[PDB]
Figure 1 (cartoon, rainbow, N blue to C red):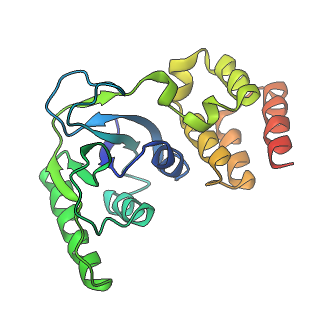
Figure 2: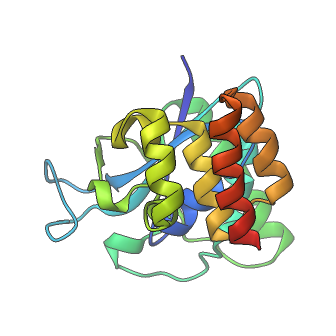
Length: 205
């Protein structure tokens, strides 16, 4: 049982890697939300926005902290009508709504500019195609294939915390020292640990 935040802030590969590097974020999935069509997809997006679903442990990280990260990853001071990349916070309850509105106000004061992020109720979130999930890890072949076998398949891997952290590491958002502490948490048999560690070290070089 975990808490959920859904945000939109442009192409979702970067946010997936960024949020997936954060302690308290348990899993991430990218997808589409904000539109009015059912079952959108990459080449049939309708009016939906590229979005990220963050499953987080509220005992470890707060919604307010996630909002702070959201507004540090982009600076939405422009009014656009490009639905696919629009800055949006999809709130799941009135607590999230009020926290979002308050922080938006604090930002607009501290830095002087109007923020155009739309704070709207979450309707439906639609998972994106598999090739979009954990995009950087998925395209780091040896590490990806090694981890996928350890986790028992694609679905199990992309839903895991370790894949979220590994994707962040590849993107440059997590240190190798932090990554190694995350690997320790999973309690792999020592030969799997050493196999993964060797690929990860060889990537840092």
